[PDB]
Length: 104
Length: 313
Length: 208
Image (cartoon, rainbow over all chains, first blue to last red; front, side):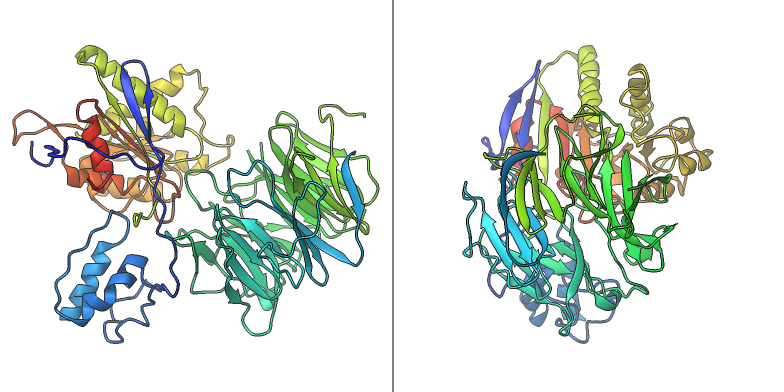
């Protein structure tokens, strides 16, 4: 049962989570997560203040999404390899796209 | 009209807000009395008394102070657009040029902010909590005299569409989610220029008000549902949403303080037993569990409105 | 916390073994979860087959219709919420029609070629309050939901020849569509599952 093995035997609940007891079936009520608190001078990137050359193909985007803007400098400026750790909804495709504009 | 408390104020009052500082707040927190000159800001001190420290420092009248971030208050005034958090920070935009923001309104996220010449903006608060400004800021042909964002249903953060006023004596309806921004969704003709366009539920019913006291209710959907009308003193239709008795309704004023509301889904347009008015909106506290901050002729008031299933008091 | 839509998760398992009664209890959890969504929302259900997309659909029809049209009519009223478009686009490729006159719909690649296209863009045009569909329809184009629900999490693997807990990449893929970057704010994510793999399903809702 690989990828369903769950080699970890004990799990950790999120912040506002609890267990609700129903008639023979259980529910886990799990609160949602909050984005990181805004740091000073912590600014996302526009597609203008990223590479002027790779500004091609960027039709349909105005300013870089938070994770792509947090990763783009290193993602493009050198052949330094990347390992991204994030959950769905960020556009990790857009970080790999900067890493590929590096090769571009 | 019942008295929780009433007081006078000097000078020229032009607006007033009532804000919280978190969704948990059982009481509204920050009453922002917007003079024509500055803003007397107070968190209710049980004898409500003056407050500078609020983090508001209003040096101009108010056009919004709003809880849209849970810990955040956005305060936009004729000078600038201040983003405020539990850290009562001022991450501020400043209205392009020396021009000044005129007509604005609040969502759960978005902030309608409308400047002279028809230059609108579009906000939306980032994954983060701090807000992002949609790159375009659209021109409008005529004077947008009012527009209200539809307060978004729980699980989402955005409207389905929104209405827009214009001075040509009609009304525009514009959607603002990435579905269509800067597309005129649907309009309707008005027998006079708009003055106030606020929304009601219980389904979604629009209320239009003209500058001469007349108002109209409608069904709210991608196109106008149906205009039902009444004539209420040739004076500005002041329109407001405020809860009552387990449900929300509209306050309106042209020459009376009219509660227009759904009595078990029943549109009644009931006067309230008080002389002419200046400005009002909802309020809560211990001294006033549910009432109206009604700032009136040279006067400011915390009022209570008793039995609302009846016709004659 | 870098995921776009704050994902509040009901990870509810069934703990019983009983199979003929489980095929009712799970349907009951479905009934209540759609009673939770029957207001202003979009409910996107994920299942592990093709015909289940339209078989759980029209069962919601039996539900809202044995509710004596109470809980049905997800709109404000009759001409409300584009009933004209709902009736005007009536005849279609597959048996979608029998439901589509009402507020229930499905998704899969099977029905036709452009059928899943016209269902996903239909939901993006703010008229499809409830859609039930398959793992391919979630893997495909970004058709998000105000709230999504994985139902059962049980797949029949021809590679394993027998029952398998569905893959984890599909989990993340269909869970990033419970709540959107634009269309939905605070994602509601329902996982109806086995109360054995339940705690594993919380370790999967986390980064453990």
